[PDB]
Length: 111
Length: 116
Length: 120
Image 1: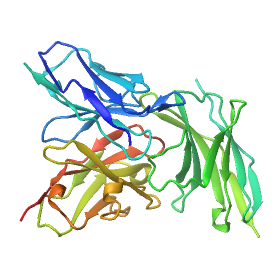
Image 2: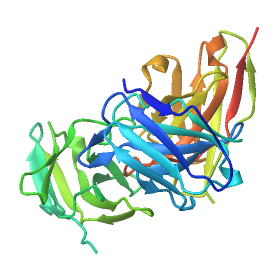
Image 3: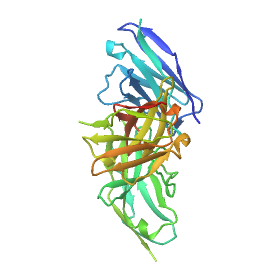
Image 4: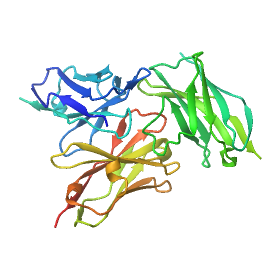
């Protein structure tokens, strides 16, 4: 069973700053050059939204200031310039095997 | 730019209980592209039997529809193991470019008739 | 254009069962597998299970293997999740989310969530 660990637990940032979020898997989630790791955004009380799929592909309609990178057990989500609408919790999720698990989340707060 | 995969042979005949092996050919297989193995459904839609790499989160995945990458880098065996009479149908494969707005290209369709 | 609209809030007692719906619209209902994930207060996101609308095949998290029943109706393009023998740890927000049937490119659309409360 693969466990996803997100760091940090909280980023207190102002608009215009760049957010970098880490997701580390207990086992590798990459095979044949594909990384089965997705990034979602959830504001509290609202439904999640897919941001990044296959760890580096930007979902259509999601602004280009979001980007994913990494492989194996180490993954990063970057918001190049934080906007007010970006204050929210961010989750990673793997699908290397069953069961599918999520990370604990990183809350991007306004300071 | 990329070309659609090819599916062979156009007509495959196997006896009940034997393995029925098609071949999907695609030369772009990489971190940019994925493969699908389909059989036409009663609704005349392509029902995904398998994928390369293995779609482990597909609900109700049946390992009896096996996909194997061959050493030559272009060919992929797509086999129905222990084929049954109800496995007769129309089969094809697809190649999916994963980059945002994933695009799909299908092969031509082949026929599998399981006899005896 | 693509929507997933779930049923309303559910208030249940322990031992009861609940059936949550998820009406899909704006797309070919069989081109996407449907999955169910819940989020409890004080817990994170937890995958419950999935169903292939074209053949009714399912997969499950072993925690829910014998208490969850997933069904679909293509004539109404609706996915259903039935959870029986509700206990207190079942209090959560329950989401349906779709995934491309060709390959796993994420849960690209989620329902709005269905609050289910188990209380005495």
